[PDB]
Image (tube, rainbow, N blue to C red):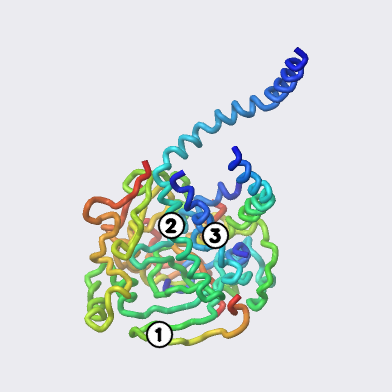
Amino acid sequence: ETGLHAYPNLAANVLNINSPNQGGIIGLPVLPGFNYLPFGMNLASTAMTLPKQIAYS
Amino acid sequence: IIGRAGGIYGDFFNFYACDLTLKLNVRTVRITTQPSGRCTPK
Amino acid sequence: GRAAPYLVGALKLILTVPFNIDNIPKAIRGDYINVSLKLDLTLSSVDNAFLSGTGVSGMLRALEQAWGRDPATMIPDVRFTPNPHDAPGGPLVERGE
Amino acid sequence: LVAAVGFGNTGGDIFERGGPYLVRGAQDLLPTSALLDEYSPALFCTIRNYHDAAPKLAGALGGNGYSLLTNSLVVGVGNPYVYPDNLPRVNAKGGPEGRPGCWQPITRDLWPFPYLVMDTGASIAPYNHFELGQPMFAEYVWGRQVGENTINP
Amino acid sequence: GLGINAPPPCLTGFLPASQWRSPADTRTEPLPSGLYCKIPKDAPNAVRGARN
Amino acid sequence: LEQLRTVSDVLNERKQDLADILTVAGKFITSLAEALASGPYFKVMLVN
């Protein structure tokens, strides 16, 4: 039951971590352990895809 | 094995870097390696 | 029936996918996955990571390619390699009918 | 006649116990049979490609025998998933080029897999260009962050 | 990916800090049940988690 | 029927292993897919 419930979301999420232009998967190094820093920053988002690469299901 | 490695501690995976080496120019520069411990051929 | 011979070989991956069942017990030593960090700071990787989709795509990719580096060992140059969507001859898909 | 009595009793008991089960199972199998029939064209190619990629993914884990060999390059991350619009959906359908199937085997002649967009509640299609992170600066004390959360980077 | 604490990790509904195991111990332990991010369906953090 | 017999025999000898797969793969799938959820990537803790 839990497999059929929570696997399609896992498949979708892992298909959303694959950047076609750079290949592979993307992960960011969180720093736990206070639990974490009060402040955070997201400087820029580089081009994961290109207009000529997008295909629609 | 994999379940315990993945998400027990929090919303994050658990990665362990036994040997970190830098690639730059096309030479390969080795910074750290672990001879013995949790990462030995097996 | 067509895919029956490859079914047993496929089973090694088709469930886990990025993990392969054969070598899990040694790579993952319990809590933490072992991994080798090969930081890439080559000009080709710097081009693909940041300067893709901009006007400075070939600013340093061609700078490195003009050197002794060969395109075979470089990460593919997305500007020209025809992926299965835009490739000549129509989209490149295989349909089992 | 005696054998008919015995066989009739046995078969009647068996069919009484296991006839409604078979009827309702064959009734409930219609949508799943149609679903499996719809995505037949993506069956042989998927199994073949996973069979081909199994040794390649196994070599990464087993080549050293103690770790996993990865090529790491720093990159920019997309904007975080927003609360109401990015919540998960299970409405995915279809396949490449609008019909179920697989892409032709990815060689280095055609390296980047064409990203496939489907009903999921999340996508990375609009990341065609370099842009600053919309929640560029964030604070986790009073929840005050600069920039506007968006689904349109 | 560059950037520090863009979404912070959630430790709510997961194993406590004092229950973490030292990286030296390669011994395997039974995997716990019912562990996921238990934030009150809010903020961009872990939007697509189990609770949704 | 005979090749189904041998396949079903090797499957029935492994019925407990199928049950183990279903049991243990249902008690961490929600936890392991949690990392992917926060953004379009996955969180990782680097102890080194």
Mark 1, other Cα within 10 Å: few <14 / some 14–19 / many ≥20: few
Q: Chain of mark 3?
A: F
Q: Amino acid at mark 1?
A: Thr
Q: Which residue is mark 2?
A: A15
Residue located at (51% from left, 60% from top): E46
Q: Which residue is mark 3?
A: F34
Q: Which-is-in-front pick, marks 3 and 1?
A: 1
Disc 3 is placed on an element classified as helix
Q: Is residue C42 left or right of residue D64?
A: left
Q: Which residue is mark 1?
A: B28
Q: Amino acid at mark 3?
A: Glu
User: What's the mark number on residue C11?
Assistant: none
Could you give the CA–CA distance between mark 3 and mark 1, rounded to whole angstroms? 35 Å
- Residue D141: image x %, image y %? 53, 69
Q: Amino acid at mark 2?
A: Leu
Q: Is residue C44 left or right of residue D32?
A: left
